Length: 219
Length: 222
Ligand SMILES: O=C(O)CNC(=O)CCCP(=O)(O)Oc1ccc([N+](=O)[O-])cc1
Ligand SMILES: [Zn+2]
Ligand SMILES: [Zn+2]
Ligand SMILES: [Zn+2]
Ligand SMILES: [Zn+2]
Ligand SMILES: [Zn+2]
Ligand SMILES: [Zn+2]
Ligand SMILES: [Zn+2]
Image (tube, rainbow over all chains, first blue to last red; front, side):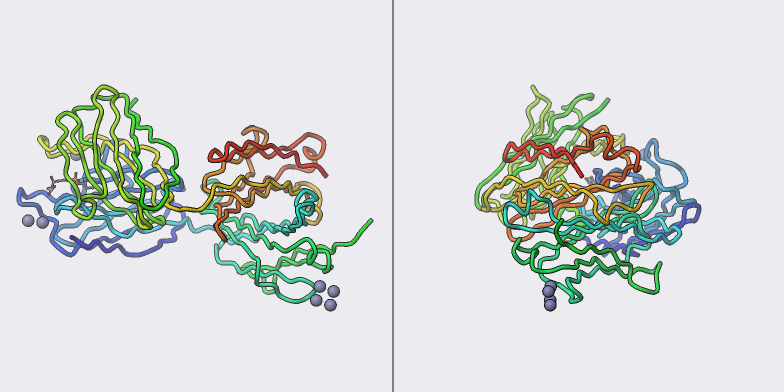
């Protein structure tokens, strides 16, 4: 089958700037009728893929002409003249010249914005959960940029690595930031044996770790 | 208005089979090819096969011969894809699409896609989730604004649906992707409101886990 290679893996562009994506094939995509069946699709976050270009450079109906395509043989390029927030997502090139049809690995386009420091919230276990003999401490680190961040849990001054569950959202369309959730789960008994629970983060926006903690007690 | 509606998420036992449906409307079903595409872990797309409902003519990617079987019901304008003897590699999201290439014209009409059907191949048991409210202590963000949360944990399989105030509250809501750990999923969502809204007015987390017919609402109280 034809192998399709896309470069780069990720593209980070500021709104208003141009973007370019490359797609290379293991066989020329020139069909025997002289047409080249190379398509470009966009899959927006949480949406089904949609075709942007067909026959190398022909735009599908309703697609903005800020987007253009070119190439021939084994080398193709998609260019976005001026990036807008709606361009965020993964772009794939897919060839239909050789059976079976094959796709490239995709290129994620991320909107490059001004650095944003996380807004951190920490939550102790609910009474409901404690009742069941479990205890989860949750930390939300909302709206930060860049995406690169390191979160560690510390209980009474010592780092806890077991029982941690992390999740991240994709880049937000509304403000181009990312959000993260980190949950530390322990037994009710152990939870009730410690005092200080700290959610600690490392991010570009700070020379020192960003901290959020609470001390559990009674009254 | 051309539309393709796909069936709901499936949890299948290893070695069994399933039939996925793709109901179409808004166009002449028998006049266009319908293609099926597979997506694994995210960025990994593969072309499976295509069928021309008018004649029943199908073409398969060699890899899927014996794995996929396409059929189409002209009287109901529904295309089907049966997957046989399910295994690990079959867990994926499958899309049907009225791709739009018109061979005679050597050109294309607009492509329309179904929303996708997630298939999970596992022998793990269906488990209802426990919903926990998260009221601020330090995660109150001083004054001005306050963030609340909802912790959904210990369920199987995906998906679970979560809203705030029945969907009336969607601004400043962040719902995190479920993460699997020891055969169970955990998901969480946070909502930020102004100090003037909560606790004065109620904020409730609504959770639905279709697979276990669980519908639960949790009021976040101080
Ligand atoms: O079939 C061949 O051997 C000869 N080639 C042709 O007839 C041309 C087919 C061109 P096409 O753009 O429709 O191919 C496709 C079809 C569906 C795709 N998708 O992603 O769903 C991706 C590509
Ligand atoms: Zn060929
Ligand atoms: Zn050939
Ligand atoms: Zn200690
Ligand atoms: Zn000690
Ligand atoms: Zn301790
Ligand atoms: Zn101690
Ligand atoms: Zn055209």
